Image (cartoon, coloured by chain):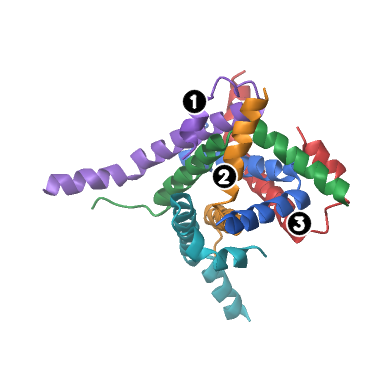
Chain colours: A purple, B green, C orange, D cyan, E blue, F red
């Protein structure tokens, strides 16, 4: 949606601390999600099914 | 009573002028992504 | 500095005319409900 | 309160992708929460209570 | 067509007049703090 | 930021049920977070750190 609009005007809003906190929290959430996804077993399931193939 | 609403809405207007909506959307979607991750952790999906 | 704020407020106002606020309320309440269930699944309540 | 307003605007807002994503996320959250509540031991607590009296 | 956007925006305006922005910021930050805590719980940090 | 504004506005908009629910949810979240931050093992690690030196 408007995430690209946020990316276009990053320099003009990075001076606000709220935006910095929001960006850091989003990056942390994405990192934690990726960790969970690649350790819980979802990827293992995909590999298992491809191995069967 | 109009004074109270005008002040609270001025706060909202300033926040909207300083924080892009794209960042709010990114934060919400990242939180939802992480929550789905912790769900798939709690369900102990096995390879078997 | 008014161009930046006007642009950001414009995108906010466009969003508010498309996404109903009741849907935002429902999403927030559902996420809170799921968070509460997560906490109860972490506290490990036994029948004792 | 305003939730019913959303429940009467459904034919007029279902065409936006953001609204579809929000509705799907809310339904998924509610379902996952009910799944947790079903298998959290809470029901076992309730039954144990009834057993006691 | 503009009636729909106007009614949705009117709902948003009423909410902004009644709910303070500090309250929603507090809610968002508290939920983020709780999410960090549950990540720490899931990842099982060691003591040794 | 304006959280102090929210504290200055407590008597004025405390009658809204939405605000009561938001306050209760925030306080509950903070308490659950503190519980996790105190039971997860963070304290254990920092106490072992102090034990070492």
Q: Specify few, some or many for label 1: CA neighbours under 10 Å numbering under 14, 14-19, or 20 or more.
A: few
Gap between marks 2 and 3, in whole Å? 29 Å
Q: Which chain carries label 3?
A: F
Q: Which residue is drawn at 63% across and 37% down?
A: C9
Question: Which corner quadrant holds the C terminus of chain C?
Answer: bottom right
Q: Which of F16 and D50 is in front in this view?
A: F16
Near-viewer residue (C9 or E40): C9
Along the line of sight, the residue nearer the viewer: F52 or B6: B6
Residues at marks 2 and 1, CA–CA distance in whole angstroms: 18 Å
The disc at residue A8 is 1
Please tell me whether mark 2 or mark 1 is closer to you in this view.
2
**Residue D5's mark?**
none
Label 3 – label 1 distance at C-alpha: 38 Å
Which residue is under mark 2? C14
Residue F33 appears in view: yes
Which x, y percent locates residue F19?
75, 54
Write the residue at 65% across / 63% down: D2
Q: Name the mark nearer the viewer: 2 or 3.
A: 2
Q: Residue at x 51, y 64 (%)?
A: D10
Residue E26: x and y in percent read 70, 42
- Front of the two marks 3 and 1: 1
Q: Mark 3 points at which residue?
A: F20
Label 2 residue SS: helix
Is the N terminus of chain C in the top left, top right, bottom left or bottom right quadrant? top right
Lateral position of residue E7 relative to residue A2, left or right: right
**What percent of the width, then of the height, locates residue A7?**
49, 27
Q: Which chain carries label 2?
A: C
Q: Is mark 3 on a helix, strand or loop?
A: helix
């Amino acid at each position: 949606g408007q995430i690209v609009t946020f990316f276009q005007e990053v320099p003009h809003v990075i001076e606000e601390v709220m935006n910095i906190v929001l960006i850091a929290l989003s990056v942390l959430a994405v990192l934690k999600g990726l960790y969970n996804f690649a350790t819980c077993g979802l990827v293992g399931l995909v590999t298992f099914l491809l191995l069967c193939g | 009573d109009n004074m109270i609403t005008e002040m609270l809405q001025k706060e909202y207007m300033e926040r909207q002028g300083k924080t892009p909506l794209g960042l709010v959307d990114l934060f919400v979607f990242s939180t939802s992504f992480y929550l789905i991750s912790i769900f798939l952790h709690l369900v102990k999906i096995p390879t078997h």
